[PDB]
Image (spheres, helix red, strand yellow):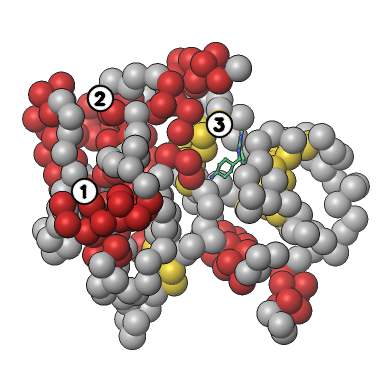
Amino acid sequence: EEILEKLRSIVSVGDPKKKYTRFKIGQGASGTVYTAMDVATGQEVAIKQQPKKELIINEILVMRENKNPNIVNYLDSYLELWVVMEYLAGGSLTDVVTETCMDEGQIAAVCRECLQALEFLHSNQVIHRNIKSDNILLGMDGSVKLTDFGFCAQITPEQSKRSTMVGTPYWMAPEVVTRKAYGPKVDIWSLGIMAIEMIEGEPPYLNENPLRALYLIATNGTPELQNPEKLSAIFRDFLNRCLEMDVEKRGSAKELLQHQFLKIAKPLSSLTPLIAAAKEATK
Ligand SMILES: N[C@H]1CC[C@H](CNc2nccc(Nc3cc(C4CC4)n[nH]3)n2)CC1
């Protein structure tokens, strides 16, 4: 594995115990996450800490070469990995969508910020491929930022398509599920599933097993709203252009950013009551 000396090349010297001090907020299997504070300017930071480390390289590379206000900023890296990124204290969007009710103004605000991140990434030939509420972090000010870039596909005019099944089943686009040639608009499909999260609390088929869900997406196509009557006609229009089977007819991030639905978006400060509610429900 000479891929390991490629990772040693990217990282910073050290020592890490001299810039950010120290302080265990959340943890999955793909590493664990912590918190800290910069000694210099007084900035507060988050730090994530075998199998398949090539994803890690891809995550660090893509991150530091695609900086954007709607993307969780990469900062530093040391030696497991000591990936340092900015700290968003509001937490994940998963907590908000599963524990609170969001009105269409709040949903619109989030969709807009996410579309801004996707319009930026796609214009830099990067497909995220794992959009879901779990990879949306919230600031205490209501900022909305995209994270988790390990499954990013870097495309180019010579190979602007992929056909591998990557992502998370409930959020994957039909073309990805059926191993067809797909592009950036798969992120738009995943965004649409995330919008359904924000409405109904979870993606379609979440009560089914991953394979059954995978099978259902492959055969059903566009998912159904339980109560489509609760939504406005312009929100439903927005949804149907995210979740179009015809990739040619599905909306890109650029053209979706101009949809009439995003016009009723509330200020991001309207999200802070959702955050406070999520945290109360979480405790
Ligand atoms: N799929 C995602 C699931 C949640 C995981 C971290 N959990 C968490 N919990 C509370 C606050 C917070 N904030 C936070 C993290 C981070 C960096 C690490 C990315 N910045 N801000 N992050 C990240 C991966």
Instruction: Return the residue at label 2.
Output: 104
- The amino acid sitting under disc 2 is Glu
Q: Which mark is residue 200?
A: none
Q: Is mark 2 within 8 Å of ligand 1?
A: no
Dot placed on the residue nearer the N-terminal end, 3 or 2:
3
Asked if the residues shown at circle 1 and circle 3 are in contact, with their CB atoms under 8 angstroms apart, the answer is no
Please give left or right for residue 247 compared with residue 171 in the image: left
Quote the CA–CA distance across marks 3 and 2: 21 Å
Task: Give the SS element for disc 1.
Answer: helix
Q: Which residue is mark 3?
A: 91
Whole-number angstrom distance, CA of label 1 to CA of label 3: 25 Å
Q: Residues within 10 Å of mark 3 (few under 14, many from 20)?
A: many
Q: Amino acid at mark 3?
A: Gly
Q: Where the C terminus falls, by quadrant?
A: top right
The correct choice, above or below, for 234 with respect to 170 in the image is above
Quadrant of the rendered image containing residue 37: top right
Tag 2's secondary structure? helix
Q: Which residue is mark 1?
A: 242
Q: Is mark 3 within 8 Å of ligand 1?
A: yes
Query: Does residue 152 sit above or below 89 in this rendering?
Result: below
Which sits in the foreground, 152 or 117? 152
x and y, in percent, of residue 237 in the image: 12, 39
Q: Residue at x 23, y 53 (%)?
A: 217
Position of residue 276 in the picture relative to residue 14 (left or right): left
Q: Could you tell whether 226 is left or right of 85 in the image?
A: left
Residue 7 placed where, x, y %? 72, 72
**Residue type marked 1:** Cys
Q: Residue at x 17, y 57 (%)?
A: 219
Dot 3 falls on a residue whose secondary structure is strand
Ligand 1 quadrant assignment? top right
Q: Nearer the viewer, residue 108 or 258?
A: 108
Q: Residues within 10 Å of mark 1 (few under 14, many from 20)?
A: many
